[PDB]
Image (spheres, coloured by chain):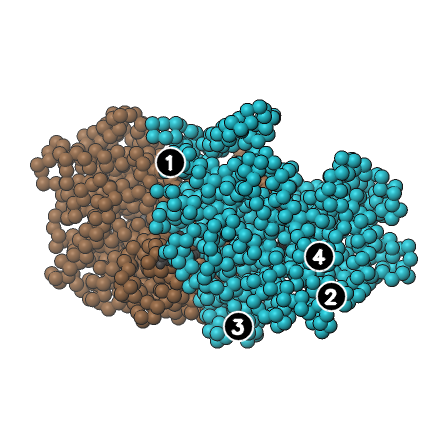
Chain colours: A brown, B cyan
Amino acid sequence: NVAELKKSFNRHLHFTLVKDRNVATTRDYYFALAHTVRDHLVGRWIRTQQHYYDKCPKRVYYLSLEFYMGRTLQNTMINLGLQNACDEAIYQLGLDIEELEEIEEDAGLGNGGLGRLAACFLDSMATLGLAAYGYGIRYEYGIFNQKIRDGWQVEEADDWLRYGNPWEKSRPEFMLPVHFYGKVEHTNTGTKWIDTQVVLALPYDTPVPGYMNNTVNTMRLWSARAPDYIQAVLDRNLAENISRVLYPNDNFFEGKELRLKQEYFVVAATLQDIIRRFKASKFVFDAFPDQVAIQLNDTHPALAIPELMRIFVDIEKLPWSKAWELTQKTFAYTNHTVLPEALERWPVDLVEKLLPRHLEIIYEINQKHLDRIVALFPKDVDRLRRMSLIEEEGSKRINMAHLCIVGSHAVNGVAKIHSDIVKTKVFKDFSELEPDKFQNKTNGITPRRWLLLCNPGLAELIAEKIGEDYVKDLSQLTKLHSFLGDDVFLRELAKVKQENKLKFSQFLETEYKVKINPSSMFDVQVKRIHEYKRQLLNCLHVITMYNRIKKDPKKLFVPRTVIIGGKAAPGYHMAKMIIKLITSVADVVNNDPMVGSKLKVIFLENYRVSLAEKVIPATDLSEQISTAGTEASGTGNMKFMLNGALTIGTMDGANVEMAEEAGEENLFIFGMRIDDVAALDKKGYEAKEYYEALPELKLVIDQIDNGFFSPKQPDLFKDIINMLFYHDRFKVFADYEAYVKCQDKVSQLYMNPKAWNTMVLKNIAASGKFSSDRTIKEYAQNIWNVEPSD
Amino acid sequence: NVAELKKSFNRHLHFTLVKDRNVATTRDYYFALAHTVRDHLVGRWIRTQQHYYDKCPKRVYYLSLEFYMGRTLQNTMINLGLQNACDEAIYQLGLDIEELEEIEEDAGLGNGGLGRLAACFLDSMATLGLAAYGYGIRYEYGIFNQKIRDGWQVEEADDWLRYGNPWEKSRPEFMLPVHFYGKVEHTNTGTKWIDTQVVLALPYDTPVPGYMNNTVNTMRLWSARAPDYIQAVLDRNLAENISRVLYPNDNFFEGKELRLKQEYFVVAATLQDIIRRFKASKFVFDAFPDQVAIQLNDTHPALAIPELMRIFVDIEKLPWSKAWELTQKTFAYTNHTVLPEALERWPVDLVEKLLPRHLEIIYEINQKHLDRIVALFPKDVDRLRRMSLIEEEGSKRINMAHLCIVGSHAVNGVAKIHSDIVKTKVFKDFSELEPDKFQNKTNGITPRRWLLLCNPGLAELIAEKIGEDYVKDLSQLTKLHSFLGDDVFLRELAKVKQENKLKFSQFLETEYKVKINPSSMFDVQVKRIHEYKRQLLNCLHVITMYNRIKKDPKKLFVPRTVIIGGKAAPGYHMAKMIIKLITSVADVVNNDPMVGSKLKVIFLENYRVSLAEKVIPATDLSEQISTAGTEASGTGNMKFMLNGALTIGTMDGANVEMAEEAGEENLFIFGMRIDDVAALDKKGYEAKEYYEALPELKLVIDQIDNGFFSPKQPDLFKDIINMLFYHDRFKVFADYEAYVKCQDKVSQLYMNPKAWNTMVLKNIAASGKFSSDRTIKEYAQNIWNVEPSD
Ligand SMILES: O=C(NC(=O)c1cc(F)c(F)cc1Cl)Nc1cc(F)ccc1N1CCC(C(=O)O)CC1
Ligand SMILES: O=C(NC(=O)c1cc(F)c(F)cc1Cl)Nc1cc(F)ccc1N1CCC(C(=O)O)CC1
Ligand SMILES: *C(=O)c1c(COP(=O)(O)O)cnc(C)c1O
Ligand SMILES: *C(=O)c1c(COP(=O)(O)O)cnc(C)c1O
Ligand SMILES: CC(=O)N[C@@H]1O[C@H](CO)[C@@H](O)[C@H](O)[C@H]1O
Ligand SMILES: CC(=O)N[C@@H]1O[C@H](CO)[C@@H](O)[C@H](O)[C@H]1O
């Protein structure tokens, strides 16, 4: 109740924050309130953990390098059904609640979708009452802050721990050592990884609060530290440099020794802690597969596999065959990646230098892996070097996905189509050998963070009509199909959008130099910037539109506001270049009042979960315009649907099964299918053809190359054109023409408000499958093999 | 009260530590207790600080690179009068209080006694109700941890923030920018320090309670913060590398750029924080000195004199003369040093690169300074080069002691004989010009930490016989003179010592492979290992003793336990050596079966404030045996006196002033006075003329040299024998015999329970003056010009 909440808020401001109402900052109130919000959870965290300890269900362990968690404060109140009363306590206390919430930093401990997937899974696993966890690295700087400075991506540190974190609590008694380097020794009492360097891993808890169920899971994030003088003391910095900055590589393997360290680290820490827990409970190690599932979130924690064997073989002195069994049983692999540049393939010297014992264990696991394929395909020899864990060209390297397949019991992909590819195509060699290991698990997105919270309009609207069990069991949204008729309703829906759009448009005017049209069509494309996701393909169409206003501004133009945004990797020079252009484009279209209020181009600086939380609800057109067989699933494409945005997108990623739920027409699919792509790959890309045979496109590409958007520096964008004309693996022009045509389709619909809305009500009803609650069930019944409750 | 304490202890363990009692760690227990004790101190911390802010009384600023603060939990309980009520509360929750208390890490951000002076005064300014602060660097690593591996001091990272510190509270809103390097432009709007490099200073406040008085002052410590990509992030360390480790140079100037940075870092932050606050008060800047006082704690914070002067002329745009009149008005200097290697001589090159504006001002200040003397002494050519702020000889070196004097309105030494020599001999040139500037403030120790805390026993018995007036006014301990022939009070004193002895005897028996005689005379030299302090002298007597056992193991040898402890500085090979010797001797001693329970010798591992609080209370003899006129005062000595230990020691430092109060009969003074040494330097201290002249000494030296204590490494010690014979500034031989003769009187008087005890009582009675509460009164009156209140 409000009153005792009012009290709790002040006892902290006094005792924890040492402040009078007279002198408290905006920050100080947040902490006072956050502590109040942590307080009423501690109860159900101890019990929940206590319970999973007392009773031993099979504990889940989601081991990931990335947990894109965003903001905890509001989310926890919502999930703990304490928001309303908290909002009320802060009101009576004449404080601005929004203000306090914005003080809180993004736990930007992840790059993109996989990061948010690791996050959303946490939320559900709790809301499902599953005894799950969360194993990860407590990075001191997350994903970088993105500043638009002279139309160029500028990065800054994500110094989110500068002032602190009320959500985390250190667990010193559970601190563990981790070893790096040294030599392997071969002796009589078995084999010893002698003479090694030690980094302490200090584990920090953060509560994953179930959605109104009393379950409160742990999320364990680890941090580093060490066991003339001055310099030697200063040199401890290198060990505490393993947990410092998270790597900013969305779909790109950059094999840096520090990263390699980061990997092992979060893996040795985890498996040690996990093993301790098993033995700590009411249980040799025969029982271990039944007591622990470890989901390897992608190849990233591949190193866990050889580590588990290490801890068995070298430490439990358990006999190999038996230990190699349980590792397979325990572990599983969700494969997130396709693009070859996103596959972790580690130089061996590196591994020989850093983790020599794990190289003998990878060289060993590989050995047998081939001893079987030679007793299953004796004549065949190309299959051998096609399945080995070692790629024996120039610099020899380990395939980490190969190790995860030979090391797991269930490999999966992240959406039907993608998984279909992983199984039958990408790994046709392993799958044939035992197909029952490869399965699919289509991604999701907790309707808590992404509905209840961020669009409380929609969440409430739907709540007044059809109960609120849909927040627990989301595939209830179908019950809005009965509202397809209702006049009042469609117009009621459109209101919620308009509200969202207006409040977002204010933000957009008070941040940038742009008159935002509050009744225009919101075109949004937000994610990591990448040639594969085609923000460029978008960009051209944005130019294309400008080109339709000049020739004729008097034609009734469907007024739209383009909003592209996303963090380009530092290393990714090409993506940064796409941004500059996008911003350059933005500069021509914003100021040129020949067009004026008809079309505006906003690039969203520093896009992060809390910013996604805001823009998504105020969107009309989701842009999911990747290339045939690039997007593995997307988690973002899902939200937009669940938020009243129409999706423009390719028959790629979960966009495919998104149509399979709403209907192929209710989504704007265009461009070439994975088959059409493979057809043109046979014929091979010939960029010029469309440049010749497209009276419109060519102009766009002349304006880029001549210097319409960069005059004061005409060439600049040459780099781009060289990729577009000779090296475009994602075929920007090839699907330009379908896209532009499929863009008019959307424009012509948006004229009719009563129709768009109807096509929207269809999308929002048929977004039930994409509640991450479902994914988890699937994962539960087939991979981890556990049972939900409360 | 008893009950609420219990509830908040249980309440805190529950909500802050998120533990159930079932699994709560020893450490969780401390933290809950810590937090509970803090809560009854917050309300006063806020009032105290608002009071100052409101009424605006003149504010004292102790500017120091060192606060040897120790633990806070026990002290804080004491001053809030809560120890008793918390001893009960913990007792009832079935936990052992004593145990929790040792979980706390020593906030040892100090090298030695100078470090402890800064801490002691914080306690006293708080009690004397004064509006004072303490500004220091919040070193991530304090003075290192010390282990003994194969009889050697091993350094270890004092990692005191690993687990976190409940007694600081960050101040994210009082954060300040600091500047380094760049260049100096002189412009139409005064001069400009541009192109500079930026570190941030984030302040962390700590309560400094008063002893039962409603004033809880502040101590404000600062840590450093920043304002390939992966590599750029890691490089931020370099910045935070300025608050990283405390320099372990006890009485030594190694001049490292990092330290120069530490020194500007603390000072720059300190000054700006003082100013901003003054500008925030009721108060152009002509009020300033009447509102602010900065004591300069040795030269270390010297960069302030120009730093202010920068802030004064360049920011506030004040006319030089005005800025200078005020600089000296607000800065008061404490000289702590005697040795020529512990003066801070900064090489201009360095001070050019890192702080080029401050070098300008250091020059200008010095130009006007030579102006004065040219004016008075137009023929004294050598005086100008002597009294300058620059030492032109070779690489130009800034004498920083001059910097303080010239820019302070008061320059003090720490003892009668100290300030004395500093007035007439070490600084004659300046005091002849301004005799009045130079004064004395005899050092003192805080009797809350060094009686109420580390010694309930005395504190009680005293507080039973002559009440508790004596804590706040220690000069009451003369009221104890009335009991000199009180046989029972005498016998109840020896018992307090006994228990302290026995408890501490248990400390020793559990920490070492050595049996303690419960009735041995506790002989304790605890103090940073230094040639000048002559631990080596002590050492030699330990040998001289052992031989008096060999020469006839049937003679009555008075059983004594020699306990020597201190930390050799990393650079100090000669200290680290002497340590190996003591240990070497120790082994032999505690191992020759022919002694047994006649003489035990232990080195003190990791001697620190907390561990001082143990040994000190259980001592009979305190070695205060530096070579005459090498100790400015000492503070160690002072305790032992006030814990019923008789001193044996040179007429050096404050040991003289201890004789003044108690009378020379009641100390064991020995050796040569400053003048006796002087003559032996006018004579020349030819070293070997003793090893011939004294039979016993010969044997001791021949044994250290020929290998008695070093069979395996026989020449190991040569480095010392050589130093003794050929490079002994501190004349270990010269005062040997005197010491050894003096030693007999100790051994003899000890055999007289009544005579000894009577003496011990005279000491504790006369100990009155050595209150750091009296030292404050003197500082407050004749330097800071401020009044105590409540
Ligand atoms: O509530 C506080 N709290 C603290 O000052 C305080 C905060 C901490 F985070 C801490 F760790 C210790 C203190 Cl003491 N102060 C306060 C309350 C008022 F109602 C009016 C004035 C003040 N002043 C006190 C002096 C301060 C200064 O000079 O910097 C400014 C604020
Ligand atoms: O009281 C707690 N408190 C926490 O576990 C706890 C501590 C935190 F610092 C935190 F931030 C969150 C929790 Cl939930 N636990 C507890 C209480 C009991 F009465 C009995 C057992 C336990 N268990 C829970 C499971 C642990 C494990 O899985 O290793 C072991 C301790
Ligand atoms: C959502 O997953 C999301 C992403 C990735 O979105 P896509 O899967 O590419 O659609 C990136 N950044 C944030 C903040 C998200 O919430
Ligand atoms: C106490 O004063 C103390 C000292 C002082 O040593 P000396 O006066 O130099 O003998 C040094 N170190 C610690 C930890 C102390 O508590
Ligand atoms: C390496 C990586 O970040 N992979 C990403 O994984 C997420 C979550 O499965 C997918 O939505 C996305 O298509 C894919 O690019
Ligand atoms: C350089 C330094 O730390 N000097 C020390 O200052 C303390 C504190 O006053 C004196 O007791 C002592 O004589 C001296 O060793």
Q: CA distance from mark 4 to mark 1?
A: 54 Å
Give me the residue at 36% from left, 56% from top.
B54
| Viewer-nearest of discs 3 and 1 | 1
Residues under numbered marks 4 and 3 in contact, where contact means CB atoms less than 8 Å apart? no
Three-letter amino acid code at disc 4? Answer: Gly
The answer to which image quadrant residue A701 occupies is top left
Q: Which mark is residue B757?
A: 2
Three-letter amino acid code at disc 1? Answer: Leu
Three-letter amino acid code at disc 3? Answer: Ala
Element type at marker 3?
helix
**Is residue A592 left or right of B529 when viewed as pictured?**
left
| Image location of residue B375, percent across then percent down | 51, 27
Element type at marker 4?
loop
Identify residue for label 3.
B85
Q: Which mark is residue B663?
A: 4
Whichever of labels 4 and 1 marks the residue nearer the N terminus, that label is 1
Element type at marker 1?
loop
Q: Nearer the viewer, residue B215 or B152?
A: B215
Element type at marker 2?
helix
